[PDB]
């Protein structure tokens, strides 16, 4: 499997350990990650789509063209980028008026989208093309802990175009985390949003933290030792939001947060330093003691 | 004689005229060869419109008539009878569909719609020129009817036809008649005991001298046409001697296989050997071979030794004139709406399961209890429109009875336990018939039932207690509610029954967007189908309540009694025939007919094909496949269709 | 320029599907002109080839769903005939895409509308079929 | 009291026009199918902690109340798509909210924090750009000091600038190219 | 007429035409039942055929008469919103 | 957000008991017949200049919202009887 690795913004510029963890985990699973040189912001679908739809799709199609020129499909570890690039590709394939508008704009920069790019999320790529059995085979250090799985919103939704199954009762990530030796604990409002999406973190910070606080509380009540996600933004919201929750609401949890790549990395014998678990705002050390 | 065509362009008020420029189409029709009269009128099917055609046929000596209007599926018979009254053969009449196929679908493209109407008129005129006079074939009508489905609708049709003096056959799939009405405890808006009022009709139909009841039987084949149907009924084997069966029920105690009781909607557990419900008609037991292990333990306890595994199903061949489909409906499966947690949460039930829990002869002995701990719920929530008015589940229709049964069952629970708190989560309360609005007023005023306008977003279970929380916006307050309940009842909608696909193929009938059976016309013929001699009655035609199903049962009896009473019906002579001078007996046609009409025979010392006219249904498959052109379907001959194709581009 | 599309629809489920689209006011392009037959089994290569000869830019055929034919199996014969016809059209220089066959029930008014929209757009993009012009020389 | 004079009859059409051809006329016209059931509001995570009611936003668009564009409420949607998944009338709720926000931004109702995030993509090509700490972190982890992204590629940065100017997004957020900041 | 939006005439007029010339149906228009006596299967009814003041068998229904009548009566069929003549026909498809 | 714990389920019955026997059980029990049409609110002279909505007071009673007794809104009714005269469900 060969895929143009779209990095995005938060993973490459904030949580770099998530990148390093993905690079080795995907290599161990037999996936050749090729550099998507010059790739910019996806751009953020909820944030930019809200300011100007034409700009969101035109800039998204510009990134798709990079992978199309390389003659390979795209892979990403972020729901925001997945949702943005996947919905852009679908819309350009299904709507010719939108494709014409975008190609008329891309002609100014010597580009043209032809509709040959398929966008994939690393979690579903692992579930449908590689297999959950291959995860267990590569487990060097079984992580026997309770995990509050966080699917996010832009991973499975909208189901009408994603076609990755149920968004109300999914099993995809639960089966992937359970393959590392962990246990996906069921909690209240499991499929609810972390609160960061749609530009809410930047404009209404306290509102976004109220939703993250509820998710953390529900995970802790379910007996979770940590929470696993598939989105650098959800990861940021859970990891750094706790500092803001402590400074704004006065509530302290010190709840460990691990990205699926970082969780898969720990399981595949990666060194916590190579995984960069120490950099996290909220210390992962309490979780490292449990494993 | 050369064709003399009369072209009539209908306006249909403004349905056609408002989009298509009818006067301009009328002027264009006059430029076509053989067209000698062309007129446009507001309503061609009305008395003045029909009299105008008749008067012109006589005054202008027309031998062809073209009506550019609605669909032939609606008024082709109407105009055929109109032209026949003026002396013109009904097969010299041609329909041009410029409403459903043009004005109604090209409303924002008036000019192109007008040009399309001109081409459709030219295509009609082109086929009309080569149409030939055909003799309507007169056929006899077998004085016997067939009713498929023994629910309140089917029972009513059979009783009415039987009471009229017509021999009737009633086929019921399950071991007993009664349908879903037998599963209900009470019935809105009178709150009468459902079985206590249906049982007399079940008793009446079982001993009626003009009704032959075939319970635990299915129609496996239907062949023929109106007045001449040849049906095959498979009398399923109960593996228990029917006549030696007492109906006591002592051989079930020993059976080791537990099957979920269908009659109790899966809540109850029955054995492989059983009786649907205590008031079943006919009152006899049955063995389910789909779950039977053939251990023979039941036979050891059985005194009469009625148990016989060597029983064989009997195929009964019967001849009938008319058929009435009254197979009912099934309750919607709410597992798909995952946010509600049906099939996941123990205390989330459907309304049909509640009917059984409430029913005295039910699995809980008439006690409403939580399936998680067996305790009576103190707080109950009803969720309306589950599986209805929902594009996500593909059901964009109103199931018609859910508002009323939710309010009814809420009154029944309040009567049994007044302390119970009941909230109904709705969008619109649909209490549209006689005494329904009053029933709704009564539910709130007398029984204290509460109504929350707001369709719930999701149901959340407390894993510790089994209690459920209903998340919904109270739209009348603009606030989000998160009330807790001991039991959540999903007011499930109606869907076609599981066997509907099998019955559709056997009868050759169509379905409407809601997946129920299609009536010939929503207002001109609510219980007829486009297939002559086949009628509909009850919930299988669309979601509806008991009086509506009962009225449809009676309506179907009247409509199905017309051909029987007449004793003679007319069938379309659009059949295939072989030109002996051209057929060299290649045998290609023989296997193409599913009815076996074309057959090879000896004529003038050589082999040729010949069609048994009576077996031809007029599909046009064998003439299309004939390599010599000897085979032709009257009214759809290759030359006629060829001119119709030319008519789209030029006058032929 | 506007495409000239000819249609062949069976009287039971398809003609009924086109009527449902009309009753529900489901708008679609006005290029098609429908011809009524009792069954799709009545449709054979000669009618489609005759339509192209006359100047059709696109030919559409509609029948009951496989297994739901009013006459039990007329649509199975037409299905075998159309697959051969698709490749014969390509051998004659007629784009396979100029012929479209679909299975539409009486309840499928929305499907008929979208099939009409899709076929119209497909033929509009291909441009006019120049057979008649070549034969008129 | 709401009078006819306070309502705009074309509000729904104007929202639908703004959504044509992106995300699509059929997508945004779905707002006309809303039957005010409240399923969207009950599913909203933001609605449980604010005065924001998803259903009322659709109601305002249909009634013609222009103030919905000036409201802070439309900006409380996190675009989780839960309402979109559960709407029984197939209303593409999330897409309609993003479309209503486009008209809000054109009216000048765009938060400063959002114009800055929009400026980061215009200036550096990313909403969250790399800093001195990013370089030193990536170095110690074993990754390339600077990721192969638009931030460190003038060709790609100038490509986006040409598109942004053509789309008029720079004028929307009020960005001055000479000063390199928002007006 | 909902939900097909057919004209009311589409379904009704053919039925009106059929019932008026049916060999087994005797139509008494502009008539009223004034008395009913008896029981099931043995009813004795009195029908009052109201005088139209026009010979039905000789009448053509052309309406040349309506164009000459000088008195205007509110049309009951149009709910008082229309004006008819003393000599009238309820509606054109009557 | 309104939870079950914030509601007083017997508020409607409590209001009825306070009305028995004056002005009468049948008179006050009429609050259960309300179908939230809004005719009372549209007829209210006070509602045209305040946040008072007659229909919402009846709703708050049927739902069990305790604050209705602590609200200033119930004291804005001038007892003009216009809603009483126009109610199609005979709500006194
Ligand atoms: C929860 C609930 C509550 C309701 N409450 C009320 C109420 O209070 N009042 C009211 O008026 N209505 C109520 N209804 C509606 C009511 O159930 C229907 O009006 C009624 O059952 C219609 O009867 P039917 O004969 O048309 O179909 P059915 O009652 O479903 O009977 C159909 C019969 O045909 C048989 N059958 C099926 N397939 C075949 C086959 N292939 N061959 C032979 N036989 C076959 C079946 O076994 C069955 O006996 C309620 C519905 C539900 C779901
Ligand atoms: C990450 C954070 O930026 P800083 O880490 O503060 O530079 C954040 N920005 C944003 O919200 C920019 C939009 C990011 C969108 C990510 C979509 S997955 C904020 O200002 O709170
Ligand atoms: S099978 Fe035998 S034991 Fe069972 S009910 Fe019939 S007679 Fe009684
Ligand atoms: S033979 Fe069949 S019906 Fe009888 S006891 Fe065994 S499993 Fe039950
Ligand atoms: S009858 Fe009532 S509950 Fe049933 S679908 Fe219609 S509105 Fe919904
Ligand atoms: S297909 Fe034609 S030629 Fe062949 S046997 Fe039949 S009628 Fe004769
Ligand atoms: S046309 Fe031919 S194939 Fe069709 S029913 Fe008649 S004889 Fe049979
Ligand atoms: S869920 Fe859909 S129909 Fe219901 S209020 Fe929201 S947008 Fe409207
Ligand atoms: S998409 Fe927005 S309005 Fe819809 S549920 Fe999510 S946050 Fe609420
Ligand atoms: S039903 Fe047909 S003939 Fe009668 S008015 Fe309507 S379109 Fe014309
Ligand atoms: S003039 Fe009047 S009364 Fe005389 S035939 Fe004509 S319509 Fe009848
Ligand atoms: S007028 Fe009557 S029924 Fe209508 S809301 Fe007011 S009190 Fe309730
Ligand atoms: S009686 Fe009170 S609530 Fe009713 S209209 Fe008068 S002031 Fe308003
Ligand atoms: O913040 S965005 O809504 O644009 C994407 C969240 S993953
Ligand atoms: S009748 Fe439709 S395909 Fe045979
Ligand atoms: Fe009784």
Image (cartoon, coloured by chain):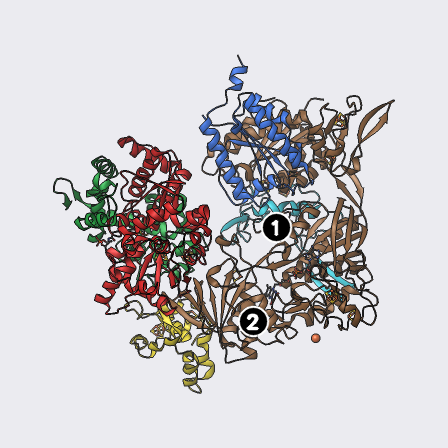
Label 2, secondary structure: give it.
helix
Residue B523: numbered disc: 1
> Chain D is which colour?
green
Q: Is residue B65 left or right of residue D160?
A: right
Q: Which of B89 and A14 lies nearest the eye of the viewer?
A: A14
Q: Which of A48 and B289 lies nearest the eye of the viewer?
A: B289
> Chain C is which colour?
blue
Residue E42: numbered disc: none
> Chain A is which colour?
red
> Chain F is which colour?
yellow
Residue B409: numbered disc: 2
> Chain B is which colour?
brown
Q: Is residue B584 left or right of residue B428?
A: right
* Mark 1: few/some/many CA within 10 Å (<14, 14-19, 20+): some
Label 1, secondary structure: give it.
loop
Res. A164 in view? no
Q: Is residue D18 above or below residue D82?
A: above
Res. A171 in view? yes
> Chain E is which colour?
cyan
Mark 2 vs mark 1, CA separation in Å: 33 Å
Badge 2 residue CB within 8 Å of ligand 1? yes
């Amino acid at each position: 499997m060969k895929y143009a690795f779209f990095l995005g913004c938060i993973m490459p510029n904030r949580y770099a350990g998530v990148e390093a963890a993905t690079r080795t985990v995907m290599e161990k699973l037999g996936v050749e990650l090729v550099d998507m040189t010059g790739a910019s912001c996806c751009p953020a679908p909820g944030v930019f789509g809200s300011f100007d739809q034409k700009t969101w799709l035109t800039l998204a199609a510009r990134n798709l063209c990079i992978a199309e020129e390389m003659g390979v499909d795209i892979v990403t570890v972020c729901n925001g980028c997945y949702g943005s690039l996947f919905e852009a590709a679908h819309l350009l394939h299904d709507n010719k008026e939108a494709l014409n508008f975008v190609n008329e704009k891309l002609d100014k920069v010597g580009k043209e989208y032809k509709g040959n790019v398929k966008v994939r999320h690393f979690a579903e790529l692992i579930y449908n093309d590689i297999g959950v059995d291959k995860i267990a085979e590569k487990v060097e250090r079984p992580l026997n802990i309770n995990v509050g799985v966080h699917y996010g919103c832009h991973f499975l939704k909208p189901t009408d175009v994603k076609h990755l199954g149920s968004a109300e009762r999914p099993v995809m990530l639960d089966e992937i985390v359970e393959a590392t030796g962990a246990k996906s604990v069921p909690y209240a409002d499991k499929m609810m949003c972390c609160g960061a999406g749609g530009g809410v973190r930047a404009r209404e910070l306290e509102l976004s933290l109220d939703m993250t606080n509820e998710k953390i509380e529900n995970m802790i009540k379910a007996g979770a030792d940590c929470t696993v996600n598939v989105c650098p933004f959800c990861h940021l919201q859970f990891d750094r939001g706790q500092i803001e929750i402590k400074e704004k609401f006065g509530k302290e949890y010190n709840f460990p947060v691990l990205h699926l790549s970082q969780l898969l990395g720990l399981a595949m014998g990666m060194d916590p330093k190579d995984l960069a678990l120490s950099v996290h705002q909220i210390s992962v050390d309490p979780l490292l003691k449990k494993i | 004689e050369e064709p003399r065509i009369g072209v009539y362009v209908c306006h249909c008020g403004v349905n056609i005229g408002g989009t298509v420029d009818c006067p301009d189409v009328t002027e264009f029709a006059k430029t076509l060869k053989n067209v000698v009269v062309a007129r446009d009128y507001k309503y061609m099917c009305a008395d003045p419109g029909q009299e105008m055609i008749k008067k012109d046929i006589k005054e202008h000596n027309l031998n062809r008539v073209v009506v550019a209007a609605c669909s032939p599926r609606l008024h082709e018979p109407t105009f055929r009878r109109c032209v026949a009254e003026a002396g013109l053969n009904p097969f010299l009449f041609e329909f041009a569909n410029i409403r459903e196929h043009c004005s109604w679908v090209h409303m924002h493209e008036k000019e192109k719609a007008t040009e399309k109407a001109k081409d459709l008129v030219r295509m009609a005129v082109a086929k009309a020129r080569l149409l030939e006079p055909l003799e309507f074939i007169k056929v006899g009508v077998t004085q016997r009817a067939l009713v498929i489905g023994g629910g309140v609708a089917g029972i009513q049709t059979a009783l009415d036809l039987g009471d009229m003096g017509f021999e009737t056959i009633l086929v019921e799939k399950t071991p007993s008649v009664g349908g879903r009405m037998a599963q209900l405890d009470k019935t809105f808006p009178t709150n009468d005991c459902s079985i206590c009022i249906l049982a007399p009709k079940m008793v009446d139909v079982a001993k009626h001298p003009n009704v032959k009841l075939y319970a635990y039987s299915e129609v496996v084949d239907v062949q023929g046409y109106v007045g001449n149907f040849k049906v095959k009924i498979m009398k399923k084997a109960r593996y228990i001697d029917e006549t030696k069966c007492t109906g006591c029920g002592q051989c079930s105690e020993v059976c080791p296989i537990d099957v979920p009781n269908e009659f109790d909607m899966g809540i109850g557990m029955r054995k492989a050997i059983y009786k649907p419900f205590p008031q079943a008609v006919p009152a006899k037991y049955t063995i389910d071979k789909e779950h039977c292990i053939e251990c023979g333990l039941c036979a050891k306890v059985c005194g009469p030794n009625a148990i016989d595994f060597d029983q064989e199903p009997e195929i009964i061949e019967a001849e009938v004139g008319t058929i009435i489909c009254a197979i009912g409906y099934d309750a919607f499966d709410p597992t798909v709406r995952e946010e509600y947690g049906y099939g996941v949460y123990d205390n989330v039930v459907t309304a049909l399961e509640l009917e059984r829990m409430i029913n005295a002869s039910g699995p809980t002995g008439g006690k409403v209890i939580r399936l998680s701990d067996g305790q009576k719920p103190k707080r109950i929530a009803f969720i309306q429109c589950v599986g209805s008015r929902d594009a996500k589940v593909g059901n964009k229709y109103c199931s018609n009875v859910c508002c009323m049964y939710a309010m009814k069952n809420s009154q029944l629970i309040k009567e049994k336990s007044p302390d119970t708190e009941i909230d109904i989560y709705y969008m619109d309360i649909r209490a549209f018939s006689k005494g329904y609005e009053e029933f709704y007023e009564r539910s709130a005023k007398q029984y204290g039932i509460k109504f929350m306008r707001g369709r719930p977003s999701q149901v959340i279970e407390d894993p510790e207690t089994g209690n459920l929380v209903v998340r919904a916006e109270d739209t009348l307050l603009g606030e989000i509610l998160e009330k807790e309940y001991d039991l959540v009842v999903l007011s499930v909608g109606m869907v076609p029954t599981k066997s509907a696909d099998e019955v559709q193929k056997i009868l050759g009938i169509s379905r409407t967007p809601d997946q129920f059976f299609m009536e010939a016309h929503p207002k001109l013929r609510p219980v007829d189908t486009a297939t002559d001699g086949v009628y509909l009655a009850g919930a299988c035609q669309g979601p509806k309540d008991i009086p509506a199903s009962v009225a449809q049962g009676s309506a179907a009896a009247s409509r199905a009694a017309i051909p029987l009473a007449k004793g003679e019906v007319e069938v379309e002579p659009i059949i295939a025939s072989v030109d002996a001078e051209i057929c060299g007996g290649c045998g290609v046609c023989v296997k193409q007919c599913p009815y076996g009409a074309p057959r090879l025979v000896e004529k003038d010392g050589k082999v040729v094909a010949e069609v048994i006219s009576a077996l031809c249904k007029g599909c046009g498959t064998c003439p299309a496949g004939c390599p010599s052109g000897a085979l032709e379907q009257d009214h759809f001959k290759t030359i006629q269709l060829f001119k119709q194709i030319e008519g789209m581009f030029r006058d032929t | 320029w506007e495409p000239k599309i000819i249609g062949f629809c069976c009287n039971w489920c398809t003609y009924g599907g086109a009527d449902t689209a009309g009753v529900g006011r489901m708008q679609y392009p006005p290029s098609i002109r429908i011809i009524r037959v009792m069954c799709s089994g009545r449709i054979e290569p000669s009618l489609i080839l005759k339509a192209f000869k006359e100047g059709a830019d696109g030919v559409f055929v509609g029948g009951c769903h496989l297994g739901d034919c009013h006459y039990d199996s007329g649509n199975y014969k037409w299905q075998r005939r159309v697959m051969m016809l698709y490749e014969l059209l390509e051998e004659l220089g007629i784009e396979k895409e100029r012929l479209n066959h679909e299975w539409i029930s009486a309840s499928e008014g929305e499907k008929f509308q979208n099939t009409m929209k899709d076929f119209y757009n497909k033929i509009e993009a291909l441009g006019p079929c120049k057979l008649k012009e070549e034969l008129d020389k | 009291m709401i009078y006819s004079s306070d309502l705009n009859k074309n509000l729904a059409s104007q929202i639908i026009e703004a959504g044509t051809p992106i995300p699509g006329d059929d997508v945004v016209s779905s707002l006309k199918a809303c039957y005010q059931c409240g399923t969207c509001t009950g599913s909203c995570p933001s609605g449980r902690r604010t005065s924001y009611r998803t259903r009322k936003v659709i109601r305002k668009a249909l009634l013609g109340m222009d103030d919905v564009l000036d409201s802070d409420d439309i900006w409380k949607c996190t675009t989780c798509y839960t309402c979109y998944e559960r709407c029984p009338r197939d209303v593409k709720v999330t897409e309609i909210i993003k479309t209503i926000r486009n008209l809000a931004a054109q009216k000048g109702n765009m938060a400063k924090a959002h114009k800055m995030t929009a400026m980061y993509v215009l200036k550096y090509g990313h909403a969250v750009p790399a800093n001195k700490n990013t370089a030193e972190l990536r170095k110690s982890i074993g990754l390339s000091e600077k990721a192969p992204i638009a931030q460190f590629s003038e060709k790609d940065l100038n490509e986006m600038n040409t598109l942004i100017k053509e789309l008029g997004f720079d004028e929307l957020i009020g960005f001055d190219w000479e000063k390199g900041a928002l007006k």
